[PDB]
Image (cartoon, rainbow, N blue to C red; front, side, top):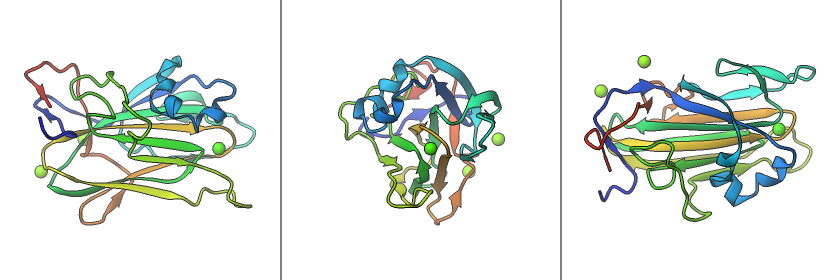
Length: 213
Ligand SMILES: [Ca+2]
Ligand SMILES: [Mg+2]
Ligand SMILES: [Mg+2]
């Protein structure tokens, strides 16, 4: 009720993020700075692929000469012009400070945390943002010189309560050449994990009795 972030869910759970690839269109590089497109506008694009069960989402790709790759078990994915969304329920094992990090992103990524900005507790497809400041993290790779790597890293930390579920939604864009999406989590003791296994979860359809916010 007054949690403003957390869901209470009593249902069979499944490991992993839901990953969805959207249709890149020419000129989307200019939209990586657009607060409408990066929050909900991309949901107007055709969904090309959808899978579930991703617990280790980070990747770094650059293979000139071969423009496609296998991403999360999806074959023939264009990694140079990529629109990628992750959605899942983050579950705290203990009460304490958990972190979510986006490191050296190329080209751009945005992170929404909590039921008011990521998605609705009982409907992962119910997504709407109220303002352009709803995000928890936003990063874009701007050439700060002669370097080939984004030197910026971002971390969102929040005190979470044990047993509760927190909606998490990311959107990642690669415009050209290198694709770097390094998305990690941090435990209250400071341990940084690249694999979200046992912390990121999915549910099927949820009734009013199994889901409360
Ligand atoms: Ca790039
Ligand atoms: Mg398991
Ligand atoms: Mg336990």
